[PDB]
Amino acid sequence: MMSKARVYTEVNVIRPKDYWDYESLIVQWGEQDDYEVVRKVGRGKYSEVFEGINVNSKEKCIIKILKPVKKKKIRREIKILQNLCGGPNIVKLLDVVRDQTPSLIFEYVNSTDFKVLYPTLTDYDIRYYIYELLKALDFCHSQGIMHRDVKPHNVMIDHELRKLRLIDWGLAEFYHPGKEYNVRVASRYFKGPELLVDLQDYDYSLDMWSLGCMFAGMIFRKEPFFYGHDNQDQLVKIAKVLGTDELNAYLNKYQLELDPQLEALVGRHSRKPWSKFINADNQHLVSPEAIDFLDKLLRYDHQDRLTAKEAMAHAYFAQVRAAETS
């Protein structure tokens, strides 16, 4: 029996085919002359990022110049950005222009890099920003979409405005129950066990593992938390913490077999309690509720992880939920 999402299972079934059939998307291009590059903001594997301006309004934007890319892949990101445009803490696609090739125009966000920000984040900042990120995840999941590349680099945080935006939807996909996906998604350190053991019928829960990796890195001040030197080593790094008994049960449940070369690397390991990662430098960020929350994200079995909605309801976010009401 194929694995299926515990939540939002049927969202794309009841949608018109036009909603998820991104491959048939007719892109309505603007014109490049409407937007102008000001300063380079960053480099990427698929694109170059620039801080730019709308010439016909002096309005500042982010310009993402997509490098070489297939027609199918460009339409997937554009269609998904359009489908999600307006949701909480989702980056907003303003326009799509081209010379060929393309170029995506987004709203501007004055982001601070996580390598500078996270070491200064307080216990409350972490609870606050993770909660904001969960808003984004619950929304895109409820719209039948998995992000599949959750990581600090794709979470833009304006620390003075205390805004958060989930960006780079280039690896996102539509969730269709029963579908086998590519496991070569996400970024190494944030890859869920499903991608490392070749479980292809995964779902939204993949994003919750990635979140857990981010979360562990923040509260334990350990970046990245799971530091594998390749995809096989990535599993080993996880097994040395979660332990191999839980790994074996998970493989058994989904009738998975590790190839012998990977099996030799994984070996045998006892579970390392989350408390073993507490030290003098990070102790102010760790509490019984933070550990319980993290422990419910970082499970081998994707079905056993908290959903975005369940995560928002966790006691770790009690103060943030109450402080938000007003």
Image (cartoon, grey):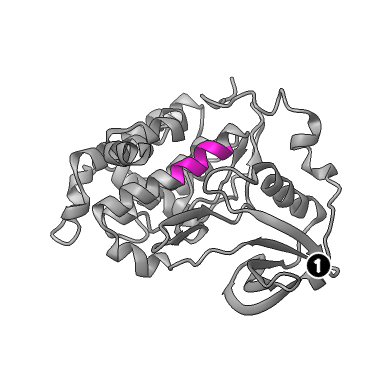
Quarter of the rendering occupied by the C terminus:
top left
Say if 105 sits above or below 256 in the image: below
Q: Mark 1 highlights which residue?
A: 101
Answer whether residue 243 is visible to the viewer in this image: no
Give coordinates of residue 199: x percent, y percent. 55, 36
Residue 313: image quadrant is top left
Question: Can residue 235 be seen from the camera position used here?
Answer: yes
Residue 193 vertical placement versus 277 (above, below) = above
Binning the other alpha carbons within 10 Å of mark 1 as few (below 14), some (14 to 19) or many (20 upward) gives few
Residue stretch rendered in magenta on the structure: 133-140
Q: Which residue is drawn at 86% across and 68% down?
A: 100
- Pinpoint residue 40: horizontal percent, then vertical percent: 60, 78
Kindly identify the residue that appears in the image at 62 percent across and 38 percent down: 145
Q: Is residue 141 one of those drawn in magenta? A: no
- The residue at the point 27 percent across, 59 percent down is 221
Which residue type does callout 1 highlight? Thr
Give the x, y percent position of residue 23: 81, 44
Asked if residue 25 is positioned above or below residue 65 in the image, the reply reads: above
Q: What is the x, y in percent for residue 142? A: 57, 32
Q: Residue furthest left?
A: 280
Give left or right: position of 8 versus 134.
right
